[PDB]
Amino acid sequence: DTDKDGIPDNKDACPEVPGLKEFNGCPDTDGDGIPDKDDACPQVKGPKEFNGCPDTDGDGIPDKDDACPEVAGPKEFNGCPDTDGDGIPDKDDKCPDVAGPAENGGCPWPDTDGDGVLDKDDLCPEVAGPASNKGCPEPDEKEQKQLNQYAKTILFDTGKATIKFQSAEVLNQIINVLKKYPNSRFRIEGHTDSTGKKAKNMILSQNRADAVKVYLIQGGIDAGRLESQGFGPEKPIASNKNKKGRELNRRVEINLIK
Ligand SMILES: [Ca+2]
Ligand SMILES: [Ca+2]
Ligand SMILES: [Ca+2]
Ligand SMILES: [Ca+2]
Ligand SMILES: [Ca+2]
Ligand SMILES: [Ca+2]
Ligand SMILES: [Ca+2]
Ligand SMILES: [Ca+2]
Ligand SMILES: [Ca+2]
Ligand SMILES: [Ca+2]
Ligand SMILES: [Ca+2]
């Protein structure tokens, strides 16, 4: 007995190390029943299933080989869980509990304003709008009428295209409405009645439309977003055979360009 463990030298698998009889004179350091020479975790108790290495979380992958030794996970990801099953392990999944594309981490593409147009596709991500306008709001039927109700109030000097001072208030109201729709374009329209010379009314209404466009530009609205057009008497909304009708036909409109 060279190492004095009780097991004869010839029948001592490890004759240099004092061990135990059960393992042919070889030591079992951690006492788990698997001798050191066969124990992949010789100082830590563990089942024979993993060669004396413990499987703490119980996913069938011993801690030594478990990339996430405390959380159960499939062998596909070396012991790391993919809870929502989007192929991205929780530890690298920005939204571990909701399946999502890899390019957005592991979260589904968000829709902040909830108009159904995803943030990455929503030209106006913070304001609800229809998808036909890339998620940007645009005036409905009743607001377009509202906008033209303001434009009706825009007054000019008789026979001239100079905007009267008193209508500066309604114009700024018009500006704020248009600022509410940054991505939309608008046609400024000048309309007269059929009284007098049509040729002169075409020029006048154009000059008046131009004037209103100029005012909106200085009020903040980008020039490229605006189109000015004189119609003369070419687009009546009322009869020209009576005074009240003609008064209705003399107007400025500010219409959404579709
Ligand atoms: Ca011995
Ligand atoms: Ca021995
Ligand atoms: Ca052991
Ligand atoms: Ca062990
Ligand atoms: Ca494990
Ligand atoms: Ca694990
Ligand atoms: Ca996942
Ligand atoms: Ca996810
Ligand atoms: Ca949206
Ligand atoms: Ca939007
Ligand atoms: Ca035009």
Image: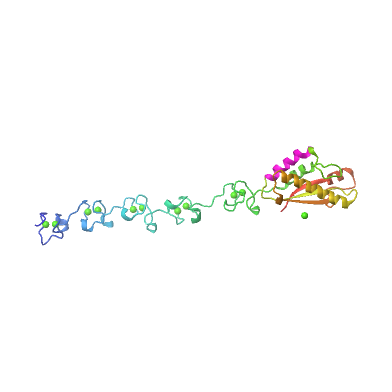
Residue 77 in view of the camera: yes
Residue 194 belongs to the span the image colors magenta = no
Decide which of 34, 139 is in the foreground and name it. Answer: 139
> What residue is shown at x 21% (from left), y 56% (from top)?
36
| In this view, 27 is above or below 113 | below
> What residue is shown at x 72% (from left), y 44% (from top)?
218
Decide which of 172, 78 is in the foreground and name it. Answer: 172
The residues colored magenta run 166-179
| Numbered label tally | 0
Decide which of 101, 156 is in the foreground and name it. Answer: 156
Q: Main secondary structure of the magenta part?
A: helix
- Residue 234: x and y in percent read 84, 52
Decide which of 201, 141 is in the foreground and name it. Answer: 201
- Residue 98: x and y in percent read 48, 51
- Quadrant assignment for the N terminus: bottom left
Residue 170 belongs to the span the image colors magenta = yes
> What residue is shown at x 85% (from left), y 43% (from top)?
247
Q: Is residue 240 left or right of residue 24?
A: right
- Residue 27: x and y in percent read 17, 54
- Residue 112: x and y in percent read 57, 47
How was the colour assigned to the protein in this rendering?
rainbow
Q: Is residue 48 left or right of residue 78?
A: left
Outermost residue, bottom side: 10
Q: Is residue 211 left or right of residue 66?
A: right
Residue 101 in view of the camera: no
